[PDB]
Image: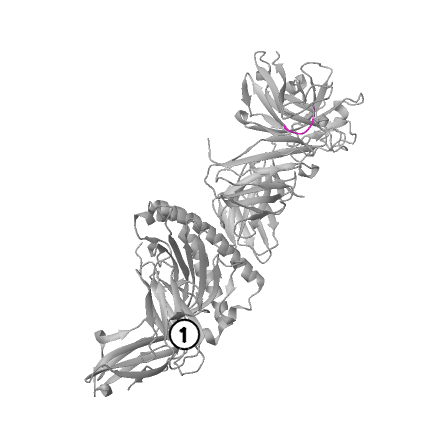
Amino acid sequence: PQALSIQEGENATMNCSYKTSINNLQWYRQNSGLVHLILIRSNEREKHSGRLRVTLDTSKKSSSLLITASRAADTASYFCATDAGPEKLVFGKGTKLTVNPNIQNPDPAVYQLRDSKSSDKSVCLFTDFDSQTNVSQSKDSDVYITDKCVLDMRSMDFKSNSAVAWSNKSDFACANAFNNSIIPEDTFFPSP
Amino acid sequence: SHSMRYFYTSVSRPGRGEPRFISVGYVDDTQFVRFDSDAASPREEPRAPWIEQEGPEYWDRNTQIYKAQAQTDRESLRNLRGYYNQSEAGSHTLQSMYGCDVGPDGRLLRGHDQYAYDGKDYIALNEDLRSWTAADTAAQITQRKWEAAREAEQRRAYLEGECVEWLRRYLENGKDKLERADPPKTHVTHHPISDHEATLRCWALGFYPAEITLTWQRDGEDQTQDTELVETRPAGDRTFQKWAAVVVPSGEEQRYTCHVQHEGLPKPLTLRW
Amino acid sequence: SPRWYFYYL
Amino acid sequence: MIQRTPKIQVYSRHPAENGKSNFLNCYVSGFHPSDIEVDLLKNGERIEKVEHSDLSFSKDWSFYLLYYTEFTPTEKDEYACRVNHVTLSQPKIVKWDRDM
Amino acid sequence: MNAGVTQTPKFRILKIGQSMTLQCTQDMNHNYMYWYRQDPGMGLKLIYYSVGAGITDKGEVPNGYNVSRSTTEDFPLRLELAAPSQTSVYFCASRQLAGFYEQYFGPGTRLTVTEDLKNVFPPEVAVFEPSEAEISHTQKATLVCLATGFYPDHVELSWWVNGKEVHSGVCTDPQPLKEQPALNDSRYALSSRLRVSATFWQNPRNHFRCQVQFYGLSENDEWTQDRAKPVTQIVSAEAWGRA
């Protein structure tokens, strides 16, 4: 599967190809129902609208889409469709685009959070790392570790990354939860 | 100079099926393709010798374009019936003609994209290829819609590039048959209508393309308003015919000449009886 | 060849 | 919808010569609407194997068709074209005049 | 209220051999309608399409399905005898014309086909309170919601602060995790976070609720197992701010 990761503000370029002679190519996006983005005709080499620019090369049977100044809501899978006769479209393989926040004051930490009801249950939260840190899946199949998630506190204009880990193992504790990942050496580990 | 044109005709026939759609394509005065939705297995078919060579993808692509077109004309016909407040029981006709005229250089002289409803002008793309002539208030409905959707800009691509490029391909295929004019053969007949007057008829036969001028002169000046002309008529094997006739005093047939103007003549023929 | 282009009146 | 009655011409592909194969033509033009009936007649009776061209139309939108049949004329044989169309109260017959 | 394509139901579980009708309606007066299926991470494949009322034709993967188009507005897809290969997301779409026109999509129907309904389980939901260390270190406070043990993965997780739904400061995992990644039938787990200012969390009149809508069995479905019938239901957990 094709995938592309960038930082907000950067430009993203994605490519697709097709197999038959065509009359038009349409790019779509999908996240969360496809939504159409831009259409280019076989007589055209470049077209743009707003932050999008599409190109088409019929010799190469290929098209590129350029998104200028990527934002968080660009995160999505992007697909091409081409005509297969006047009345039908055929759709290709997507590219998964992830637009990461620019964390300007990283403050990596792992915290322990207790259940509202039976405080003996808990979860580990790794948070506030910069977008270069990658969270690995667990070695052990009784330890669950989510992927990274970006949250946006809009009124405070503040974004942050986190991942959640939990387990019933008696060995499990926040100090070792994320041992499978490469985390910053100055990650704050408060006492349990 | 040359042209390629497609001619589309949809005819509703309520209670007796879906509308019939027929299309024909012409390079200058030569028909080269047809499509008829009422055929056994409807498909584009060759109608000139030099198009037969085209492969099954040619035929398939076009066949699919015509079937798709025919389906949109069913909706257009319903729209039109509504604009003109007409009943569902009547048969109606939508005709469409589009294509390209090119000069000696082979680039676009004039683009065409026009429509008629029930045999009268409905809407036509103007020669600047940027605006439309609507024929009546009903057609202004279509005009507003097509102005809003930027129809004319979208139509320009085919009319300026692709139309022109196909025309060139087809000129290559056809060679002499398409590029060299076939001159009028001729004859003059004479037929007394009384003891003092006769008919002289000038004949122009087996010619191509259809454009021709036939003119009766006496002593040099043209016999303008006393000439009978018939419409130019197809011979049945891709050539054309015409005649022009004038009634003259008997014993004066010597005063009269018939001037024949056709692209296949090094110089204007002058015929006598 | 006919145009690959579709519309409604 | 103005309806427009057909113009009709009957003629041969080639100048005639008796006993020689040819085509009898009946050219119908200028008409609207497009439904029309056209028969070729030999000594007054319909001929059986008549083809016609594909429906097309002129600049003014009026339709034209060519009806035709292989024939060989003989001196006693009389030919005509019979045409019906919504604009005709009764059908119309146009004889081929071999003496034009 | 906007124009567009709508589809029902949002979610469906079927036993192998059952049948179903997916509804699609649009109000744009579009003549051209399409059904596609999409497996997760994959591309759309056309099942059937229609150029207008009374006309339908087969797409790339028609087998197993039928359609009809009696009106312009609706294009129902019929699933005749469910098989495990038909687990997928089904998307309806429409456009105005042939040629140079883009399609508008519905939101999708998420279908799980299962050999036996005993595989279906509702989520348990728990809320985990912010740590005092996070509050001291950052002056912010992250709550975590965990939804666990559910099958199929047909859930919608929402956060409610003092009775009103919030989106700011929330991130919910895109994909569930499998609790038993080796099993085809594994139950799932889903986490979400809601982050607020410490002063907000320190107000004991602030009320925080994680709610999970689970889409499960109908009144129509037969249940002969011992445990509670895993019907469509909302499961929730709550916490109050803490001085």
Please identify the residue farthest to the right as the structure is shown. Answer: A171
What amino acid is at disc 1? Leu
> In the figure, is residue E110 to the left or right of B97?
right
Residue D13 pos. (x, y %): 41, 76
Residue at mark 1: chain:
D
Q: Reply yes or no: does residue E152 show up in magenta.
A: yes
Q: Is the C terminus of chain B in the top left, top right, bottom left or bottom right quadrant?
A: bottom left
Residue B3, relative to residue A44: is it above or below? Answer: below
Residue range of the region highlighted in magenta in the rendering: E149-154
E4 vs E237, left or right, is left
Figure check: E118 above or below E41? above
Q: Please state the horizontal and vertical placement of residue E62, each as a whole percent of the image.
A: 62, 45
Q: Position of residue E211 (x, y in %)?
A: 61, 21
The residue sitting at 39% across, 56% down in the picture is: B95
Q: Is residue D29 visible?
A: yes
Task: Tell which of C7 and E61 is nearer to you.
Answer: E61
Does residue E107 show up?
Answer: no
Q: Compared to A154, does B237 lie above or below?
A: below
Mark 1 — residue? D24
Q: Nearer the viewer, residue A91 or A71?
A: A91
Residue B182: quarter of image = bottom left
Quadrant where the image shows the N terminus of chain B: bottom left
